[PDB]
Every structure is written in C-alpha cells, then in structure tokens.
Image (tube, rainbow, N blue to C red):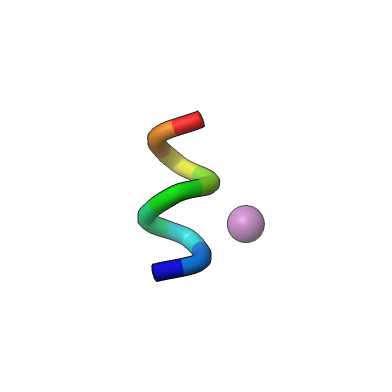
Length: 9
Ligand SMILES: [Co+2]
C-alpha cells in the first residue's frame, strides 16, 4: 500500500 500511494502521488 505505502508505495502504491507514493507512486500515485
Ligand atoms: Co514511498
């Protein structure tokens, strides 16, 4: 989850 979101951002 953490990196899914940071990539999206
Ligand atoms: Co990150």
